[PDB]
Image: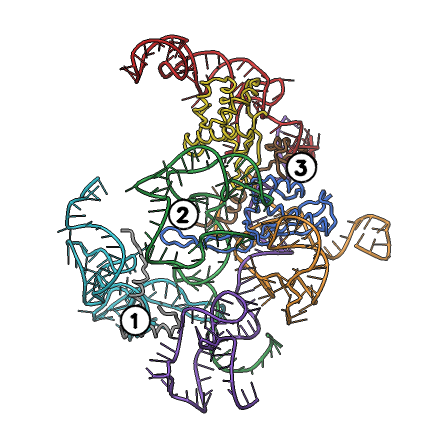
Chain colours: A blue, B brown, D yellow, E purple, F orange, G cyan, H green, I red
Amino acid sequence: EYPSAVAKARFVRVSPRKARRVIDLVRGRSVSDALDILRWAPQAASGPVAKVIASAAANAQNNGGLDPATLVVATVYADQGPTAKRIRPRAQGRAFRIRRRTSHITVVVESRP
Amino acid sequence: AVPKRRKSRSNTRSRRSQWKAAKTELVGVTVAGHAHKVPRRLLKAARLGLIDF
Amino acid sequence: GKRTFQPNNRRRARVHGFRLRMRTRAGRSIVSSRRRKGRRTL
Amino acid sequence: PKPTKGPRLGGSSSHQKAILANLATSLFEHGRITTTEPKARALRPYAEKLITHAKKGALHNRREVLKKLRDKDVVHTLFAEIGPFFADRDGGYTRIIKIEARKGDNAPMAVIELVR
RNA sequence: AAGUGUCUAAGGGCGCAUGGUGGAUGCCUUGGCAUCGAGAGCCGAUGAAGGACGUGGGAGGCUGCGAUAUGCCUCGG
RNA sequence: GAAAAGUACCCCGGGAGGGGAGUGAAAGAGUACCUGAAACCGUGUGCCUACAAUCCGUCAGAGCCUCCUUUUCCUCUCCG
RNA sequence: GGGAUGAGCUGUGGGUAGGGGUGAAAGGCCAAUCAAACUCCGUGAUAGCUGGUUCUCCCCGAAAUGCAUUUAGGUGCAGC
RNA sequence: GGGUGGGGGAGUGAGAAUGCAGGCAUGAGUAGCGACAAGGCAAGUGAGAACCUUGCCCGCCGAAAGACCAAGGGUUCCUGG
RNA sequence: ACACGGGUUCAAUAGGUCAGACCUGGAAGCUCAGUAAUGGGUGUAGGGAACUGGUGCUAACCGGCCGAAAACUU
């Protein structure tokens, strides 16, 4: 029904929840609307997302031969990426485990006239 | 005061859901060359050309 | 008053150096013990 | 100028004084300052009054300006070019245009300009 | 007029489809433990065991090596 | 992975990364990699829920959803 | 706030080392732990004590009473 | 690389020991971000700059936040990337 | 925070400006007296935050989003 183009970014150093709180603004919206929204998104963690969405439309345009004007974002994932751990020293010698969480963002797009 | 019991998934996700962003945008803002899209807050700057990409 | 540790390599060498270990019968056993475990000596 | 309500800029009012004076200085020396919106807003009644003294054009007014601006070159320019030019405009010597917030603290930026 | 009267899902629940994180299970092995049999059972003031430093056409370590230094001479393979 | 044959080249992107091509039996084997479960995270979607309390179940149990037999019926019947 | 030309303070150098040292004496200090430091070995220490002891099914089915106990929160014999 | 059957032998069956090793959850996108010295503007490099560079102001210690030695650390100094 | 209330150019909401209320209490320069320190005149001056009433000069943006088209009896 929707022969969508697939694009995704693995190993991004932005947490999934911080991705999701932006992604919720771009469900069922056009690519150009999403790109403008993210351009002016005060959360300022949308950069990677705009790059991925842009690459999805560009790839659909060149490999698929589709027109961005009708290209709409269908499904967006903010999957949990690989996580490392770091030790911080706190009071009384307590060694706490502090992590650096990542994400795998998967986006599919398709013309929906 | 420390957490006595863990919170049920059905309540935790409610707290996760009441943490959303606002929606502001504006179309029709013609500038030199291509007509882009900006917010009302900054449309005057766009009209004066004080924007970048 | 608020002191914890104050290194001084000459003091460490004179106190823990294996040439001091040569002084005693026991100290020689420490070196031979460490060799058996496979560790680098002082 | 009407005193603000809430925290002074930076530390105390003395720091606010240094900020307002330096901002007014480089404003008069450049004519287009892009900074934070609160600073431009607080600056409005400050620069408006300094220019009011410029269009009055008196020795006494120069010393009242010196109470605020230790730099003298900006005073020369201010009472030599700016004042006379705005002598025919009875108020409204500035203009605030909103500017995109900074990537790093999302501070509401704004640019403050003179009419020309 | 009076009465009956489905339809909301902000956001949760359950179940399916499809992904991610993780690297458990399965199968394996450059590796080890425990034994029978057969050797050797000593090294060293001729400077032992074991080490520091250094050596390669090319940064560092391991194995080998010692200002003749990832090698020399002799008899064999 | 039997063998590096470690993804030529092109395109988004500052790069990492990804897609298209290609090697390959296979990439659903891409250096973070045989097989790849669970916790956990998340998306799409069928169904219930904003006058109502109860170890968050069990048994009765309406109405929808999905699969499906017979059948009024469409006579379009060599089809469904 | 107290001492601050003194029974002073402080660095460099050295020694006394565990049933021992030290102590203008508190049973405090001896590498963040001192009514006898730490590490290793004896050592898989021991405890009449606390906690644990992993799949199922079938038949049958107790006591918390009595005696004695450096014993009454345990155990042996008897009873079920 | 495993089944069926007759046999043999177990490091053989985990839901619990304030159990152990590893990974992820709730708490939670909460607290906190580190002496009560203070930053600001312009131009510019750069895809991207409150935080870097170069200028102009402002502020602070100044018997120390300055300038030299010892112990210690062991290249943390300079250049280029 | 949000919300509330007012206003958004037929506009006096905020800023600014002119003039006021109130406060401070006699500014600088100049001139005169005084050896000087200082004191008179110019001068109820000068400075000024919130309140008052005028004054449309700047800024309130020549544009977005969500929002009914109604199951039935006597």
Q: Position of residue A104 (x, y in %)?
A: 59, 53
**Residue at (59% x, 54% y) in the render:** A10
Residue sitting nearer the eye, C3 or A66: C3
Q: Is residue B8 above or below residue B24?
A: below
Question: Which structural element holds mark 3?
Answer: loop
- Binning the other alpha carbons within 10 Å of mark 2 as few (below 14), some (14 to 19) or many (20 upward) gives few
Q: Label 3: chain? A: B
Q: Which residue is mark 2?
A: B2
Residue in the foreground of this view, choosing between A97 and G70: A97
> Which amino acid type corresponds to the residue marked 3 in the rendered image?
His
Q: Please give the residue where the numbered disc 1 appears in the rendered image.
A: C21
Task: Tell me which corner region of the image, top left, top right, bottom left or bottom right, holds residue C35.
Answer: bottom left
Q: Amino acid at mark 2?
A: Val
What amino acid is found at the position of numbered circle 1 in the picture?
Arg
Nearer the camera: disc 1 or disc 2: 1
Chain letter of disc 1 in the image: C
